Image: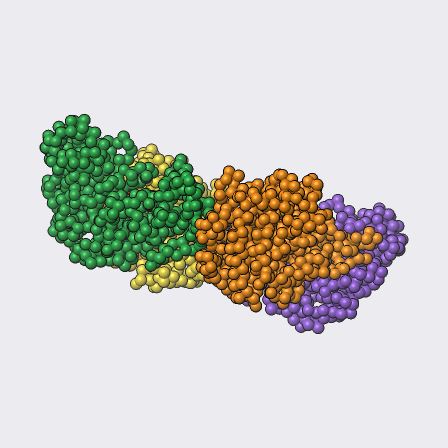
Chain colours: A purple, B orange, C green, D yellow
Amino acid sequence: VPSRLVKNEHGSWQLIVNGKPFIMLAGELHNSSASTTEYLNSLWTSLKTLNLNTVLAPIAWEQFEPQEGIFDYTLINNMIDGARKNGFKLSILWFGSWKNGESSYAPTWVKEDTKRFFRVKSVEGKEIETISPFCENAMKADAKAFKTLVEHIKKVDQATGTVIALQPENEVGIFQGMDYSKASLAAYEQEVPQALIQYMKKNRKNLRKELLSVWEENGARTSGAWKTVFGDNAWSKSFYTTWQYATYIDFISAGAKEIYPLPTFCNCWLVQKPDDMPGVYPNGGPVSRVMDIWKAAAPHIDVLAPDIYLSDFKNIVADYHRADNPLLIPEAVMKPANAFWAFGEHSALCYSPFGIEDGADNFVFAQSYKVLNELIPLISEHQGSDRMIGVMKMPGESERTVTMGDYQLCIKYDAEDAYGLIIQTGKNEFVVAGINFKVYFTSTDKKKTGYIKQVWEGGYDTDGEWKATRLLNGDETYHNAVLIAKGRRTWSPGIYRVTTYLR
Amino acid sequence: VPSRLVKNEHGSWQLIVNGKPFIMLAGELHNSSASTTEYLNSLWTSLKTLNLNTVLAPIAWEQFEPQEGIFDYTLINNMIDGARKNGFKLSILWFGSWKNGESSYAPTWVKEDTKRFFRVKSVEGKEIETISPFCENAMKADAKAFKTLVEHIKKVDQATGTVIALQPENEVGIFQGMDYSKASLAAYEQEVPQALIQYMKKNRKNLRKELLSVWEENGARTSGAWKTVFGDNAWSKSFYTTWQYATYIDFISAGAKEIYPLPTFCNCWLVQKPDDMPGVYPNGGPVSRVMDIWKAAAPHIDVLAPDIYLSDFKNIVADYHRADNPLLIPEAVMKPANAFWAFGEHSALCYSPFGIEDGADNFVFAQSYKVLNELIPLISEHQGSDRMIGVMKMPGESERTVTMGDYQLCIKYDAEDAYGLIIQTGKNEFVVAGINFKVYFTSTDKKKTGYIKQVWEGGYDTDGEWKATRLLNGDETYHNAVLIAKGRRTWSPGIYRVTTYLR
Amino acid sequence: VPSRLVKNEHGSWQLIVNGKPFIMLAGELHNSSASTTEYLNSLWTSLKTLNLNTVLAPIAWEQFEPQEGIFDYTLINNMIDGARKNGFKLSILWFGSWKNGESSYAPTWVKEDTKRFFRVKSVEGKEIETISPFCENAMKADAKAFKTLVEHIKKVDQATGTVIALQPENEVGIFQGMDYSKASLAAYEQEVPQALIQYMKKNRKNLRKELLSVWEENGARTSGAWKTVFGDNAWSKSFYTTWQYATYIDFISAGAKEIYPLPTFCNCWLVQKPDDMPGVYPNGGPVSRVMDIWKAAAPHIDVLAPDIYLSDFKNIVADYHRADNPLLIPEAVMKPANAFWAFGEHSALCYSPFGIEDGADNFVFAQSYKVLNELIPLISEHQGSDRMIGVMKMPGESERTVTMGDYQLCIKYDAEDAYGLIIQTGKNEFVVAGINFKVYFTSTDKKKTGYIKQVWEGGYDTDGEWKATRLLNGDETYHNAVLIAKGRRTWSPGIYRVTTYLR
Amino acid sequence: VPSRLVKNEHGSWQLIVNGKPFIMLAGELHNSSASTTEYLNSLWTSLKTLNLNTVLAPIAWEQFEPQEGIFDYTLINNMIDGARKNGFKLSILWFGSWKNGESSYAPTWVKEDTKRFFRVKSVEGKEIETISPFCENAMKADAKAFKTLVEHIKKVDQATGTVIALQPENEVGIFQGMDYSKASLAAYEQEVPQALIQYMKKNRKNLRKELLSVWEENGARTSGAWKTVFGDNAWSKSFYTTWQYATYIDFISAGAKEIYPLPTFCNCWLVQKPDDMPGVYPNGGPVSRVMDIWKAAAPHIDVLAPDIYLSDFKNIVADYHRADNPLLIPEAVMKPANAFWAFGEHSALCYSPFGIEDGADNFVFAQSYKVLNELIPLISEHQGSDRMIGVMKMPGESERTVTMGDYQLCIKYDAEDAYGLIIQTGKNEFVVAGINFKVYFTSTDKKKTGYIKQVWEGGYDTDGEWKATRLLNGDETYHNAVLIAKGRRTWSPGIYRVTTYLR
Ligand SMILES: OC[C@H]1O[C@H](O)[C@H](O)[C@@H](O)[C@H]1O
Ligand SMILES: OC[C@H]1O[C@H](O)[C@H](O)[C@@H](O)[C@H]1O
Ligand SMILES: OC[C@H]1O[C@H](O)[C@H](O)[C@@H](O)[C@H]1O
């Protein structure tokens, strides 16, 4: 396969694409932007102006299998063609059974057969425009379509590897405490799957407090029905609903994994505010609260991926990033700081603003992606090490101090919009990227005096070779008292090589 | 003849031009803009930028017959030539005896002979710059000139049919309770024409309340002088004045109809405010109040056409549009909403902003006319059916609900300027055109649940074939909860094909 | 001579240039703009953009005769050359003895010999930077230089006639009650010249009140010294000072007139405010107060020309324009209204903004001059007749009514900046030029009704032929109720041909 | 040598470059702008737009001798090459031991050997990032590197003379009362060098009051230790610290002077406010207070050069300019007035805004340098004479009166930004350059009347020949009452030739 997840020596998961470490400097199209060849093809030049290396774009079941057993390859073919012609990799979003909780992208022939493909019912007993995750017929039909899609991708792309990941479904779940379908009501009475129980036993001290605290308040049982093991409440309802979604979607993924295994992720509509109960967000989706349930149920899903539109960026990405869950953000705001934070602080695989085609001639964002592209080798090499950090000022913060081997770095912000990353490349050498901040280097050991030795500004050329544009000194470094990450001027992030010394 | 009015199966009158249904996406030039070949010819490129299919332009008697019996074809010839070269049809306005009530376009040789062509007198006894409608000499001279014009048009245009309609005179009437000319005073004493009496008898329950109520308050007589049948008052004065105008102008039209019958309309200066008595507007013109008198008197005039500059657009067009009177608006404001309302709600033949050459690079208006042009076949096919409506928000309105077969449509406005039209093309299919509104589809029958199935955005190509630009779903339809008529973006009206379904 | 003043049948003086009536649509350069060939030549294209037919430009004595008896033809030659190449006539300003009262343009060899060329003395006894008009040596030297200049112009221009007028000196006089030079003090005691006395006798009832009232308060004597005939006061001082200037400058002109007689004018710095006594303005200059003295003394000076920078334009031009003194304005503001007023109301020979090279791309002024150029034949033909008037609104005015044969014209202003002219070309025909006003035509005789018959907008082509651009009617003339002088649109003055009629 | 300092007949020092008087119309690059060939080469076209004749640019020791005994000629070679190709001379700044007091440009191999190259110690005993001026090893290493640099310049530039001056080090000194290094503490106890004593004896009445007053308050001794001759205080500390710096740097210069003597200057960080004690500015630098110490100690340094960023420009330049110290300003603000003041009032050798590459398309500054370039021959010829002055209005000033031979000049300012210069070129002739001021010429002798005779505006062509663009008179000189230095218009300084006369 031309795309694979591989753990490095620091325990960090890396994307390896066509034999090399690859980070998705990505963007996701608006939902309807890949619905015709002509509309998509109008976008490619726009996208290139932003220095993307990867485009996230949907394939809709309703278009792909417009009558049962009849498959239309037009949109996937043109999508791969245009990606190749314009220098992009693709992550394919499968808008099948569910997108933002609902079934609006299911085929006309699925929608119209509510007997074969039964719907979620509300507490009021109303069938909604959502296929129930307890419907096995729907599971099989989606799975067959998805597999056919992936089979096709292998048949047209197994050598080039334009397609480097897959997202089955999109932000699944129900805006309800539970599905009131008869099948759902019967499932709630069943025994808790052993696979869940054993997962909880084996990984107890690393479990989500939201799961552990509910398990333990019911006596941490190793058998029983859902209401026995987890009590009769909103959480028990959320847990078995989540188990169902992860299980349905795991089967869908399994079918693809058997014929052409690519990195696979499912994305979640986040718990928007901290008191929100399941169903105010999509109940069943892979929010961090239920991460353990998804891991237990869905081993053919590699990553649980947050869609982040909220301002509390650093806390959110820290919440989703775990040893068993690399950070992968398929939908976000068009804010360069976020990118630098995700890649530098958390070794992310992907950063991707949503509706990216809208953001053409966001010059600063484009130049940010240019600089990140220059740094992909260096970032890759340091994923998971304590020698790489991000930099991102949040309102009300003024400085960040960190230890890097022999040195203490004091990062002070010169403007509200201040961001970058810092890599220690040698005992007395650092690469600093970004804008609107300063770095003071001092000695960890107080018997010694540490100082900047020399500073160069520059970039990496197309061969990956460092080229200095200036040796910064005098005013430009306050006579080596400080690194000023002023940025590249046309202002956008710069790259600075700093040597230090101890006397 | 290459232009004709024909009633379809729904009882709606259609313009059939060169064998096909035609709707005038029109504009009228400023009054003096066709007075030389050079000034007119300077306008054509401007007009094309607005996507007109039809130009309304005057021929002035004073220029056409500058000495009695001598005819100058220069302006009509160049007008037809330029229309052909720039892809426009023409409706010819005949500024003869009267324009905005007055006789300023009559030839020098008519103006200067007030014995042969006697004037209206005021109550003070003053002769004004208006030829009296009781002057038979003036009737004959105008009629002869008009016929000569039309004879010429046949001789140069009978095959191509560049000229598709005729407007004899322009907003006729007097700013007076009545003409005080001796002939006028003698006419007021005469017997009411039987043709009027019989019209009133035959069409009593469909008569204008303004006419019926006056007739019935005088005892609904079937014989007598004007003051007998209608009482001695302002209304009796207006009625016999109107009879005179319609009769004079009918004779003028009759002469043309005999040699080359084209759709013929007379236009009115509207009753500007509801209390206004005859003479505050031109007394004698085809305002809706006297529509029955004009129909009775002038069978060679096909349509009575309002000139609408007032904001109460929907009430006005509803007032002029009758089973015997299609809506045809030769003069209006340059407001796209009005166009969509007139064509969609009332199956109008014509919408035409006045001084159109001024409005070049009114981009939104131009794109509106582009979209209407795309829809002419579909609009044509649905003229007079209960499956086509207009959409136009007025201040203080928030929604419009309508029944369309099995579905209830709730139209909600997203901005003040919200307009379009809606056609049901199938039991479960709709075409929605416009901007700044949303449509919710639900089931008429409350035992059933109705929903959007699929939504496409697109347009009709030059062959008249539908071409989708996107399948709208997800954010673009709130996951098929609603049709968002956002418009085509460059914002101007869009076209959306919606399929629905019942479960 | 290729330029001459000739009185027409209405008593009006006309400029006849190369055999045809010519009106100077003129501009005067800044003072130093003709001081090198290179600076002047940089201006010609600018000037052409303003549609000038005539440029007023200086020749400075100091440059022309830089050593006594040595003459430098460079600047006059290049000036005539560039005028020819760019389609302009020239009026030559001779900055000799005096410019704005002073002698700053006299040659270095005149300035430095205050014995040979004695100065004006102040009352304090100080010699100033002004050559005394009582210095005969200075008179002769200036006269010889001026004649040499004109001799040269004949020698290079007698056939083409690029040079069409001459201005000897520039705004002469002293900022003093009188010259206190010994020669001046001796002149004040002399007998009043008979030529003055006889002029006063012969033209008594047409004399300036300022002169007559002083003469008559001293007993209207026919002999005596200045203080006898005019009393011992400021006026007597001004009169004999003025006599001296006019006499000195007449001799200068006489020398030129003998070899090559061209229209010759002297220009005055105006009495700036009504109480100002001689010497607050240049005492001796041809202000209107002393017009009779200049006429008496200086028969080789054809015209006394006001330099008008003040806002009271209509009163000023009425004050300078007399039967023996055509209106000629060599220096004015760049205001088109002023031009139309001067040419239309007062049949002026010249209108000329000062520092004209500054005003390039004053579009409105340029288009004004274009329209005047079109009208020169028609204006010429009506100079001095009661069938041509100007139009110019001043603050606080609202209308102007005039009688033109059978018609009464009511001119009503539609904006503050409203101006043009009106010519009756036939008993029932008028040409109206301008902008921002309206004209109502009614019958002089109240037994008759007068009205507009027809209105055309247009212009005169390069052959001088009228070409209509539109027949204005309907909205454009309120149905012949009024002429609307809206202007040519791109707004600037238009030309309108109006026919009228009486019934 | 192709560049040399030579005293003219007025006692003024002139730069003679390639055989001719040369004034540096200069600019200094930002500190890091000559750190790569590519960054420098990006600037040349920018610099040419400003009409510089000279660029000041650094060579950094750390780059030039990156390992001991290994020399890298890349940056000096490319610098000379680009200067030649773009028409500039160079003054080379040697950023060696010290730049703005500190040692940030010393080689890595100097910084890292604090035993061989010992640092300054603070009063707290801390070694700082400054090489001590008492370190002989550092003196020798710097001197050897500097000499190698100059040897190279001779080897590549001895014929062309692109390099016309040298600045060893940059704003030297310590932010301390004294160096607390053991060597520094031992030096403070030593005998005052005789060379200082004798200098003070010989030049007593011309000594800086700051030095003389301290010497005399300690009894004006001719022998003793520093604390004996100058007391035990801050001044004694500053004096021996300054002696040390001047001595160290003199040795560095001496090595170069032996093989290739060019004009050499050292620049100072100014006493920023009048109460500031040594160490608030760099203690040891050539501020004016210690000018005598630098002259005594450092005969191989030709000029002590102020870096002026403060608004008190006229007082500062008067303070640094002495008979033994021409004015040379290598760092200043980009303000044209300053340039005119320095060159005109004080016959400066150099005016140079800092960060000049930033100021491209400062049009006014560029045109100022154009005009100065035109005047270099005339300025050169009048350096040190009482016939050349500067003109520069400071806030709160309104006029300046000066005597120039027979004439009194009253300079009155017409705007805040008013500046230029004035040269008397003959008994009755003046050249006035500048903008926004006026000059009134009157007679020194009150028995005589002095006046402007004639005024020309113009410039010097590429051959150095005067070319008048206009003879200014009339309005342009108020009829020779005044010279108006209005400027060249596109507004920037003009050049005006004025002749005057006495009667
Ligand atoms: O723009 C809203 C956004 O909401 C979620 O993040 C979905 O995953 C996206 O497809 C889109 O609907
Ligand atoms: O612009 C005013 C307008 O008034 C009426 O509608 C007329 O029919 C038009 O010709 C025009 O006069
Ligand atoms: O601009 C002022 C103006 O004043 C007078 O009118 C002069 O005749 C002109 O030459 C000029 O000096």
Q: Is residue B500 left or right of residue A14?
A: right
Viewer can see residue A124? yes
Q: Is residue B233 left or right of residue C491?
A: right
The residue shown at (76%, 70%) is: A70
Q: Is residue C422 left or right of residue B92?
A: left
Residue B217 rendering spot, x and y as whole percentages = 69, 39
Residue C294 rendering spot, x and y as whole percentages = 18, 39
The residue shown at (38%, 48%) is: C428
Q: How many marks?
A: 0
Instruction: Depth check: give the residue in front, D433 or D73.
Output: D433
Viewer can see residue C330? no
Q: Splitting the image into 4 quarters, where does residue A118 fall?
A: bottom right
Residue C135 rendering spot, x and y as whole percentages = 12, 40
Q: Splitting the image into 4 quarters, where does residue D78 fall?
A: bottom left
- Assign the N terminus of chain D to one quadrant of the image: bottom left
Instruction: Depth check: give the residue in front, B500 or A379.
Output: B500
The residue shown at (73%, 49%) is: B401
